[PDB]
Amino acid sequence: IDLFSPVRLGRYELPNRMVMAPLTRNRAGEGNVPRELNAEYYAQRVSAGLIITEATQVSPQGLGYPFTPGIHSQEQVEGWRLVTKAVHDRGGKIFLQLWHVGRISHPDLQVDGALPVAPSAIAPSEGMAATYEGEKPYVTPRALETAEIPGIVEQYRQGAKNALAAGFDGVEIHSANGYLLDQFLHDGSNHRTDEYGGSIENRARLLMEVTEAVVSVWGADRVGVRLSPSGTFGSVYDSDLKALFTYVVDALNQFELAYLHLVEPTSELSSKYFRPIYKGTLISAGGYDRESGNAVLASGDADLVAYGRLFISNPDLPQRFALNAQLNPYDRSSFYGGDKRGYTDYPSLE
Ligand SMILES: Cc1cc2nc3c(=O)[nH]c(=O)nc-3n(C[C@H](O)[C@H](O)[C@H](O)COP(=O)(O)O)c2cc1C
């Protein structure tokens, strides 16, 4: 098995084991609606065995950065249909990454200056909010009421139904990188004393409920979950990160989702640790190249290998890797925001 070998992923037969990782690009149109430029971009990358979209908010409440697309409105459904059609016209597979930023936002990004919501009224210790005006200090978020938790689950349920209507092949639940679900999981960011805080089971409960709701919409073989055991991004810490992720990964084996997507870490909490704990398909991401991607597949510790930055600058990464060709350099300055430049103008091979 290598990067070029076919693989089964839930209800699909993919032609290779290379995944385009989810990548926020901040290039949405009016009302956070995807646009023709975004469809071009994903279409250029269809040689990935599977594309995961940029994180996509399930509500205005759940947005935390400028110009990110949503999946809550009919207009957004119709914008994403541009993307699904473009990808499917070229025979590719695409899953939409369902997002809620939780506390990683700012009143200036919120309608009417509402506080961001979170498991607890605890600001991130580190970093700054990314507002339309520039960076600003985070404010303390508002703790969700217990009777608000159903509403959160419904945002994910409706966003999953909207993705389905838009023509995606599936969805990925973003439970990584210090966003709302991950803020629930960590006991440094979750100090609740209802059934969504306290024990590890309780801190994992919102993720389990969201996953159950999303599976009911799509079928489990069209649903993935992404987590970050060694992920501290978003000022998210926990006393026993291992045990916490050891039960969360063991609780996802009862949902039988298409895959579990892990951000790799040095911390023990790699795919080598989780392989005997998870019982499905594993996608591994973070810092891979061609050599290291083949290696992790050779080791048996992961089934697919996701690539982020190299997919930004190499739309035909799989062919470049096959032919041992040189890659285009990536320009970090145009990762987040802007126009076609550093987005759709990186060339495939001649
Ligand atoms: C510009 C950029 C945007 C990203 N946005 C997302 C996102 O929307 N959702 C997510 O789960 N991770 C996001 N990530 C993390 C990547 O999915 C991925 O794990 C990382 O890029 C893989 O490492 P690599 O770039 O070394 O391949 C982002 C990373 C970068 C550099």
Image: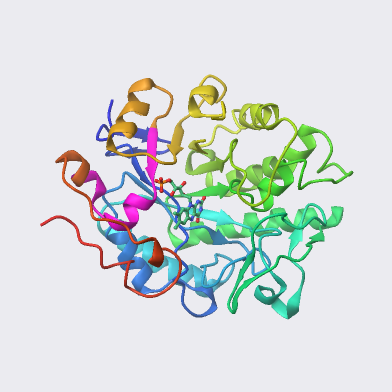
161 and 96: which is toward the camera: 96
Q: Quick check: 280 left or right of 158? A: left
Q: Is residue 273 above or below residue 292?
A: above
Q: Which residues are magenta?
A: 304-319
Q: Is residue 80 above or below residue 228?
A: below
Q: Residue visible at 37% across and 64% down?
A: 83
Q: Residue visible at 78% across and 52% down?
A: 119
34 and 296: which is toward the camera: 296
Let me know if residue 308 is in the magenta part: yes
Picture quarter containing residue 127? bottom right
Residue farthest right in this picture: 193
Residue 212 locus on image (x, y percent): 65, 42
Residue 338 locus on image (x, y percent): 41, 74
Q: Quadrant location of the C terminus? A: bottom left
Q: Quick check: 136 left or right of 23? A: right
Residue 194 locus on image (x, y percent): 88, 44
Q: Is residue 95 above or below residue 339?
A: above
Residue 334 locus on image (x, y percent): 39, 67
53 and 216: which is toward the camera: 53
Q: Quick check: 116 left or right of 24? A: right
